[PDB]
Image (cartoon, rainbow, N blue to C red; front, side):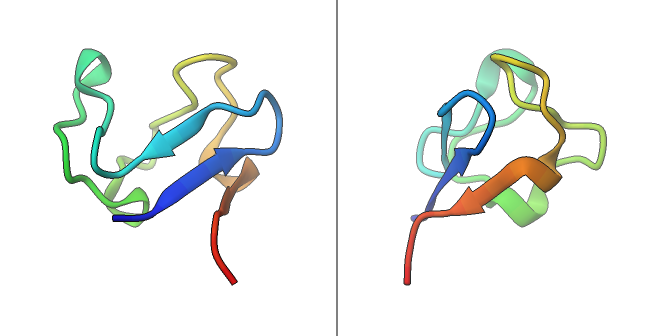
Length: 54
């Protein structure tokens, strides 16, 4: 699956890994993340993430 980088801190949201400690199971797409989901490191909103691809 895809990887998304937080343009603030560099945290990589790995869709294959998810974010289980914050209520996100593995295999959760970035677009499927809750609107109130924020980067688990710095708390940046989803608007500050960029998809790693061409």
